[PDB]
Amino acid sequence: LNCNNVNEMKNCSFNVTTSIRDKIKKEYALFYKLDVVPLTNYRLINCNTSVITQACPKVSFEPIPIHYCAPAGFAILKCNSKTFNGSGPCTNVSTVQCTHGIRPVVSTQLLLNGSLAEEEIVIRSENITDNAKTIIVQLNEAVEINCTRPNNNTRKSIHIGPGRAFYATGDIIGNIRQAHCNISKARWNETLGQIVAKLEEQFPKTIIFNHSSDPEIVTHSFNCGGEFFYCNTTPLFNSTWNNEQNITLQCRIKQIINMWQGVGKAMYAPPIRGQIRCSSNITGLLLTRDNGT
Amino acid sequence: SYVRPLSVALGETASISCGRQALGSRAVQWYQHRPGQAPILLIYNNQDRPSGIPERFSGTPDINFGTRATLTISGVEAGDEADYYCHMWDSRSGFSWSFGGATRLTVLGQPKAAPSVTLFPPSSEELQANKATLVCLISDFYPGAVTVAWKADSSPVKAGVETTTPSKQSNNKYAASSYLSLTPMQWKMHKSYSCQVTHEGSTVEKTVAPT
Amino acid sequence: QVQLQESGPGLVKPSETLSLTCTVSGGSISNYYWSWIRQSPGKGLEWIGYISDSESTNYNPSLKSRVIISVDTSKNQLSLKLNSVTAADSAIYYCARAQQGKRIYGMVSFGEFFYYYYMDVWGKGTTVTVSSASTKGPSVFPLAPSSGTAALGCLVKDYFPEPVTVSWNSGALTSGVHTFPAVLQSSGLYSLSSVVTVPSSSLGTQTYICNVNHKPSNTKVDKKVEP
Ligand SMILES: *[C@@H]1O[C@H](CO)[C@@H](O[C@@H]2O[C@H](CO)[C@@H](O[C@@H]3O[C@H](CO[C@H]4O[C@H](CO[C@H]5O[C@H](CO)[C@@H](O)[C@H](O)[C@@H]5O[C@H]5O[C@H](CO)[C@@H](O)[C@H](O)[C@@H]5O)[C@@H](O)[C@H](O[C@H]5O[C@H](CO)[C@@H](O)[C@H](O)[C@@H]5O)[C@@H]4O)[C@@H](O)[C@H](O[C@H]4O[C@H](CO)[C@@H](O)[C@H](O)[C@@H]4O[C@H]4O[C@H](CO)[C@@H](O)[C@H](O)[C@@H]4O[C@H]4O[C@H](CO)[C@@H](O)[C@H](O)[C@@H]4O)[C@@H]3O)[C@H](O)[C@H]2NC(C)=O)[C@H](O)[C@H]1NC(C)=O
Ligand SMILES: *[C@@H]1O[C@H](CO)[C@@H](O[C@@H]2O[C@H](CO)[C@@H](O)[C@H](O)[C@H]2NC(C)=O)[C@H](O)[C@H]1NC(C)=O
Ligand SMILES: *[C@@H]1O[C@H](CO)[C@@H](O[C@@H]2O[C@H](CO)[C@@H](O)[C@H](O)[C@H]2NC(C)=O)[C@H](O)[C@H]1NC(C)=O
Ligand SMILES: *[C@@H]1O[C@H](CO)[C@@H](O)[C@H](O)[C@H]1NC(C)=O
Ligand SMILES: *[C@@H]1O[C@H](CO)[C@@H](O)[C@H](O)[C@H]1NC(C)=O
Ligand SMILES: *[C@@H]1O[C@H](CO)[C@@H](O)[C@H](O)[C@H]1NC(C)=O
Ligand SMILES: *[C@@H]1O[C@H](CO)[C@@H](O)[C@H](O)[C@H]1NC(C)=O
Ligand SMILES: *[C@@H]1O[C@H](CO)[C@@H](O)[C@H](O)[C@H]1NC(C)=O
Ligand SMILES: *[C@@H]1O[C@H](CO)[C@@H](O)[C@H](O)[C@H]1NC(C)=O
Ligand SMILES: *[C@@H]1O[C@H](CO)[C@@H](O)[C@H](O)[C@H]1NC(C)=O
Ligand SMILES: *[C@@H]1O[C@H](CO)[C@@H](O)[C@H](O)[C@H]1NC(C)=O
Ligand SMILES: *[C@@H]1O[C@H](CO)[C@@H](O)[C@H](O)[C@H]1NC(C)=O
Ligand SMILES: *[C@@H]1O[C@H](CO)[C@@H](O)[C@H](O)[C@H]1NC(C)=O
Ligand SMILES: *[C@@H]1O[C@H](CO)[C@@H](O)[C@H](O)[C@H]1NC(C)=O
Ligand SMILES: *[C@@H]1O[C@H](CO)[C@@H](O)[C@H](O)[C@H]1NC(C)=O
């Protein structure tokens, strides 16, 4: 690819075979820097790793309530106890044919559109005294998150084969802006304080929040409108607790989302036309503990 | 820069469209520059104007992207004939050192007046200095386009005469000069000298003799 | 309020520093932006450059390697020094006050704004002519009338370079005054002609004198007018 810049995503061009196998065209399109690597001439990030299949531009990524049922002659057992920590014996048990409405929200660092808790916020872990064990927090009152890609991008259809139509990003109409999110400084402060509360019921000492130790794990990554954001969440967890204002993160965007198994294939999220803006409830959280603090 | 012509009628509403439409959010400036004269800031922010500009100078804002920038001049007058520059500032394009192309406004259908020709003979001093000069003066005509004809007695001259290109005035009419350089003997050997100024379709005559 | 006035040689030779200055009236020199703009015949307006209240330099890249816009805050004076001038540089030079605007379209923190500049008050204009030809003073020859109303004037013959100023009775007589545009004669010198329409009663005798001034020649002359 022969890539330029804009001001970030590149502006590339490339010879590609067409619907006729011996006729060559040179198309242009934009590719986020994460979706390309230098060899200036460029290429796609995966070409030395795995096959990539463009997701059909008609299947949606919408988290839908999935109800898990056990076969006839089996049973699923609930636990209605409004303070039930991870494991142990539950005293308010009930039986159900199917689970409630589950949304397969494939998220990272901040759980989205999940099931809240009743009464107070709970925190779960296996051996909380073992630091190499994740901590799954559950909030009792969602704190609003609002994300958007304000760029008014376009979608160009590129015929590179009989019926094989690749959808690329044409250009940006209007202002070039930044993909980001928003949460309330007040609501995330009192909610961070609630999380600080029960970080003492299993500890003593002082609580410190700090940034994360490919970028999928380092940032709040999720799906908004159909494009995968990667919001640098350092403006979220950088506070030490003894005993208006919108928090906005800097989200990048990716179109090539590899898989998590062991060197196989990848995907290409086709571009979304117009602007994108979604609103979600961050109801969970995945922490990780690592002197005197 | 090159010129872009425009013609509105006196009392109408001009719609001067910018020649370099914006790609992003814009902050467009409008300058009224009369040739050989200080420019006048018409509109700085996309619609904001300075102190001392009539309300009839309206500039379109950029609330919803897509609406191009157009300068609107309602109730055009005579003095509104000038150049207009579109200084475009948008997020995408870089630094706009260059003003607009230009849009010269020419108001049509204005009251046609006739010139006031005034011819002065050669001065006493310069005649003693061995040189002559007839100064055919023209002022307050419209439209500003005249042809000057010099007659030595009854015969035309054409040799040794300069003439100004018509220039505008404060009262929006035009004015131009016309100098005929004679030798001091030619000026005396002739009985009379005339100056024919043919404005529109009428010629005016102002003659002088050496007495 | 604030006004401006330039003052330059009016004529500079090729391959030389076209110096210039501009003093402001009624406003501080170090709390605004100042721009310089020229306009040749046949071309449009051209933005030279501009200096900030921080004394920051930024010139039009067209001629960036030539210009240098200085400023001395002891007075309200700031200069401009073009060099290696050529014939295409003959233009009227203006002195205007620029002001800074911040056009915000997204988030002020990510950098989603741009800075635009607008000139709201302008100087009057200093004509500049570049040519190896030497400077020349004019010569005034009166023009007398010959009787209700009548007209008289002064012929400013063969000068170089533009412009000349012509008052009447040092500035007293200002009604009916009508100075005419010059005439570039083939000899390379301009020619002006002022004229004043005067009541026929004042012919005898309300003294009339035209005050001619040509800056590139350090000349100031007067001349009576009478039949
Ligand atoms: C997620 O979280 C994010 C982070 O928290 C959050 O980010 C925010 O995003 C939004 C949108 O994405 C951003 O909103 C924009 O804000 C811009 C800035 O607006 C501010 O500043 C202007 C100008 O301020 C100067 O001028 C005023 C007077 O005019 C002075 O009083 C000021 O002191 C100041 O002057 C000093 O500073 C200048 C520097 O700029 C110096 O140059 C100067 O010398 C002085 O020193 C103010 O007018 C604004 O006031 C408005 O807001 C207050 C509350 O504070 C309200 O009372 C009221 O509603 C006011 O209107 C504000 O303070 C805006 O420019 C921008 O809106 C313009 O642009 C868009 C597109 O770009 C247009 O569609 C829109 O119509 C606006 O255009 C108008 O204005 C421009 C410029 O003036 C004109 O050129 C244009 O023609 C048009 O004019 C028309 O409308 C005018 C009214 O707007 C009217 O006056 C005209 O007559 C004409 O009709 C947009 O609103 C926001 O900045 C982000 N926040 C941050 C912190 O970055 C995000 O929202 C969250 N949510 C998400 C992402 O979902
Ligand atoms: C991306 O680059 C392409 C070129 O590969 C640009 O397309 C050209 O744009 C110019 C104007 O900027 C036109 O004059 C050309 O005709 C265009 N060429 C083709 C083949 O379309 C495109 O504008 C660039 N877009 C961005 C957002 O940078
Ligand atoms: C969390 O749930 C909300 C509400 O269902 C989702 O917002 C929807 O987003 C889709 C596509 O982005 C739109 O078609 C719907 O209209 C939206 N619903 C509402 C009520 O606005 C949001 O996308 C979900 N978040 C995640 C990460 O899946
Ligand atoms: C496409 O092939 C031609 C062959 O001459 C080459 O010149 C051109 O650079 C190629 N395009 C790209 C984007 O490499
Ligand atoms: C592919 O190339 C990238 C260069 O960006 C490199 O980091 C990666 O290790 C390479 N993978 C393989 C399997 O060669
Ligand atoms: C069991 O839990 C449900 C919901 O959490 C509650 O409504 C009910 O009162 C509880 N019953 C007992 C016996 O704890
Ligand atoms: C987000 O806010 C409240 C729950 O506190 C609710 O009105 C809304 O449905 C929530 N959205 C979800 C759960 O997707
Ligand atoms: C949950 O409570 C039981 C006792 O009711 C306890 O044994 C278990 O360790 C608790 N789980 C955690 C993660 O603390
Ligand atoms: C938890 O981990 C610590 C060491 O990190 C270990 O000593 C302890 O036995 C573990 N407890 C349980 C219940 O696994
Ligand atoms: C986005 O761009 C399209 C042009 O392709 C335009 O029709 C539409 O109004 C724009 N929308 C926004 C919100 O800018
Ligand atoms: C998020 O957006 C929703 C709807 O636009 C709004 O009700 C809520 O207050 C917003 N919250 C934050 C933190 O931006
Ligand atoms: C966060 O981690 C960095 C990396 O070592 C460290 O320098 C910093 O002190 C930490 N911040 C807090 C508040 O613990
Ligand atoms: C996240 O943002 C902080 C500043 O807000 C910056 O220092 C840090 O490098 C960013 N993290 C990444 C992974 O870019
Ligand atoms: C942590 O990051 C946030 C970003 O919103 C910032 O407001 C806060 O000052 C930072 N904490 C520091 C610098 O101690
Ligand atoms: C926070 O974001 C919401 C989302 O639209 C917006 O309405 C509100 O004005 C923002 N508040 C601040 C202080 O930026």
Image (cartoon, coloured by chain):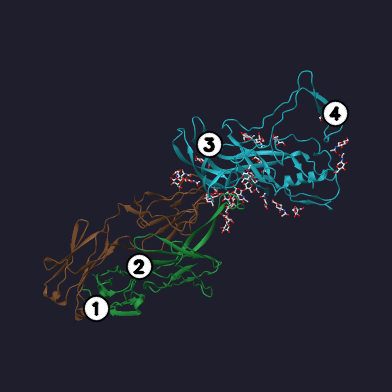
Chain colours: A cyan, B brown, C green
Residue corresponding to mark 4? A92
Label 1, label 4: how far apart the Cα atoms are: 123 Å
Label 3, label 1: how far apart the Cα atoms are: 89 Å
Q: Is residue B205 left or right of residue A222?
A: left
Residue corresponding to mark 1? C226
Place of residue C62 in the rendered image (x, y in percent of width and height, measured from the top left): 43, 61
Q: Nearer the viewer, residue A130 or C163?
A: A130
Q: Specify few, some or many for label 3: CA neighbours under 10 Å numbering under 14, 14-19, or 20 or more.
A: many
- Helix, strand or loop at mark 1: loop
Residue corresponding to mark 3? A167
- Amino acid type at circle 4 is Asn
**Which label's residue is closer to the chain start, 4 or 3?**
4
- Amino acid type at circle 3 is Tyr
Label 4, label 3: how far apart the Cα atoms are: 53 Å
Ligand 9's image quarter is top right
Q: Is residue A249 left or right of residue B28?
A: right
Label 2, label 4: how far apart the Cα atoms are: 97 Å
